[PDB]
Image (spheres, coloured by chain):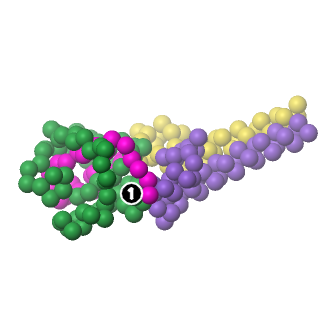
Chain colours: A green, B purple, C yellow
């Protein structure tokens, strides 16, 4: 329901899906659908199983391909200024 | 203290981030800890 | 002094650049002024 779905929200009216009390794994996501930019800031994608997070928030939204670089801690533009902007000391990363 | 970084201890960034990417954060923590150690040594030398 | 940066005071870089971009320049000015202050109090402690 969080990856490879058919209906998402917008960039200003996104939903904060509560993902907690479960086994959050990253190695079981490559068989569902291919990911274009698996970039992650502040956390490594290979160290997701060694550690354990708490109250994972799922923010899903569909944007244009030209705005894929604005989702970063400290960018500027039309999404990083007028829309949901990632914090500076933001832990967590994005799957697009 | 973070010394201008995202975390304080090196074990935190080494557990969440990768060494090839968090190398600048480790270097800032080492230089920050070395500066505090140098200040404490100079203070102890004056007290001695 | 610039301490290895493009300007001396933080009010100049904060007006031409954004804080998310000029964060490294402000950090270099802070650790540069802190090092000079550490040297000044060291000389003052020796003079005292």
In this rendering, the count of numbered labels is 1
Residue B30: x, y in percent? 64, 54
Give coordinates of residue B13: x percent, y percent: 50, 53
Q: Any magenta on residue A69?
A: yes
Q: Is residue A66 left or right of residue B17?
A: left
Residue that appears at 22% across and 65% down: A35
Where is residue B38 shown, x and y percent of the image?
Answer: 76, 47
Q: What residue is shown at x 39% (from left), y 47% (from top)?
A: A53
- Residue nearest the observer in this picture, C5 or A93: A93
**Image quadrant of residue A27?**
bottom left
Which secondary structure is most common in the magenta stretch? loop
Q: Report the magenta residues as a range.
A: A50-74
**Picture residue at 27% right of the left edge, 64% below the top:** A28
State left or right for residue A1 relative to residue B21.
left
Q: Which residue is mark 1?
A: A48
Whole-percent x, y for residue A17 in the image = 22, 42
Farthest residue, direction top: C48
Residue most extreme to the front: A22
- Image mark 1: chain: A
Q: Callout 1: few (<14), some (14-19), or many (20+) C-alpha neighbours within 10 Å?
A: some
């Amino acid at each position: 329901e969080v990856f490879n779905a058919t209906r998402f929200a917008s960039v200003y009216a996104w939903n904060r899906k509560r993902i907690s009390n479960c086994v959050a794994d990253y190695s079981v996501l490559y068989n569902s659908a291919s990911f274009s930019t698996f970039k992650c800031y502040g956390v490594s994608p290979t160290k997701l199983n060694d550690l354990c997070f708490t109250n994972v928030y799922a923010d899903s939204f569909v944007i244009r391909g030209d705005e894929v670089r604005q989702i970063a801690p400290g960018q500027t533009g039309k999404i990083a200024d007028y829309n949901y902007k990632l914090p500076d000391d933001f832990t967590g990363c994005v799957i697009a | 203290s973070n010394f201008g970084a995202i975390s304080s201890v090196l074990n935190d960034i080494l557990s969440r981030l990768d060494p090839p990417e968090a190398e600048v954060q480790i270097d800032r923590l080492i230089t920050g800890r070395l500066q505090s150690l140098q200040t404490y040594v100079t203070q102890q030398l004056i007290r001695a």
